[PDB]
Amino acid sequence: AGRIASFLKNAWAKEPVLVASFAIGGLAIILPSLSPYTNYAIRINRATPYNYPVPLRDDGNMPDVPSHPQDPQGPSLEWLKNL
Amino acid sequence: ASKVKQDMPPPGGYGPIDYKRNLPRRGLSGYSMFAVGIGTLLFGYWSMMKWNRERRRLQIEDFEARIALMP
Ligand SMILES: CCCCCCCC/C=C\CCCCCCCC(=O)O[C@H](COC(=O)CCCCCCC/C=C/CCCCCCCC)COP(=O)(O)OCCN
Image (cartoon, rainbow over all chains, first blue to last red):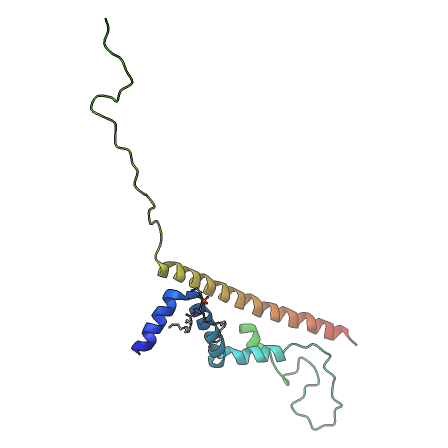
């Protein structure tokens, strides 16, 4: 409580560069685990179509696969437009 | 027959001559400069976040153009 206060004061008086560096590194380590937009970053990465989407051979038992891109089925990037 | 004329200080004397150091403070507080820097960083971060999200959307759009043209 007071020991850490005196140590931090001495460090800020003598080595401000090291204090700033350690603070920045600690924030960089800690903050990503508490952010709600990391999931958004992952989903943005998954949403980029680098390669061709190969169609599946219809067998009559896929209610959740579209037969046309404009069909309502499949993933939607409506969330991405407002983000 | 004239007075004695010589190089002399004026009657009374000379005006004061400054010699002491003069290095005025002329500076802001540390908190002020740190706050300005942090605020500038936050403004830049927000602008870059918006711009990069828009860029990702544009990249997706042209990738889909490629996908449409591929067959
Ligand atoms: C959890 C973060 C970890 C990752 C982030 C770090 C990123 C990179 C930073 C580290 C780089 C290497 C650091 C090496 C430290 C060496 C310390 C040392 O021995 O140097 C001392 C000087 O420093 C010291 O006195 C010893 C350490 C002093 C404290 C330094 C910071 C310790 C932690 C304080 C910050 C805590 C976090 C910030 C909180 C903010 C406050 C709310 C000797 O200096 P000389 O150059 O030899 O002197 C010659 C002239 N007289």
